[PDB]
Image (cartoon, rainbow, N blue to C red):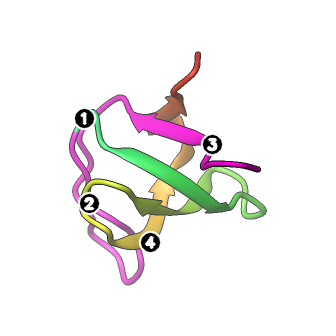
Amino acid sequence: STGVTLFVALYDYEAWTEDDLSFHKGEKFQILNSSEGDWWEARSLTTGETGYIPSNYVAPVDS
């Protein structure tokens, strides 16, 4: 709203499909789209890359 609402990776994840995003534990994300359910479109603030991430692998930072 005045800044990004941050989520953080709890676990490592290796992409294996057409549009998912690999990431390591501790990367932070802006969530771009949550409408799909258990897969969220996100941009990693660590690598700059964008794709789908499993929602059960992340948690809000100010938590």
User: Does 25 appear above or below 31?
Assistant: above
Lower sequence index among marks 2 and 4: 2
Tag shown at residue 51? 4
Q: Which residue is mark 3?
A: 5
Which residue bears the numbered disc 1?
25
State the residue lying farthest toward the top: 63
Q: Distance of mark 2 from mark 1, alpha carbons? A: 10 Å
Quarter of the view holding residue 32: bottom right
- Mark 3–mark 2 Cα distance, whole angstroms, equals 20 Å
Q: Earlier in the sequence, mark 4 or mark 3?
A: 3
Between 53 and 60, the residue placed more toward the observer is 60
Answer whether labels 3 and 1 touch (C-beta < 8 Å): no
Instruction: Provide the major secondary structure of the magenta segment.
Output: loop
- Residue at screen point 54% across, 40% down: 6
The amino acid on which the numbered mark 1 sits, given as a three-letter code, is Lys
Q: CA distance from mark 3 to mark 1?
A: 18 Å
For marks 3 and 2, the one nearer the N-term is 3
Relative to 30, is 5 on the left or the right?
right
Q: Are marks 2 and 1 in contact (CB under 8 Å)?
A: no
CA distance separating discs 2 and 4: 9 Å
**Hey, what amino acid is under mark 2?**
Ser
Q: Which mark is residue 22?
A: 2
Is 11 displayed left or right of 24 in the figure?
right
Q: Residue at x 76, y 50 (%)?
A: 1
Residue at coordinates 46% horizontally, 50% vertically from top-left? 29
Q: Secondary structure at mark 2?
A: loop
Q: Is residue 61 above or below residue 21?
A: above
Of tags 3 and 2, the one toward the viewer is: 3
Residue 21 rendering spot, x and y as whole percentages: 34, 66
Which stretch did the figure color magenta?
1-24
Sequence-wise, the earlier of marks 1 and 4 is 1
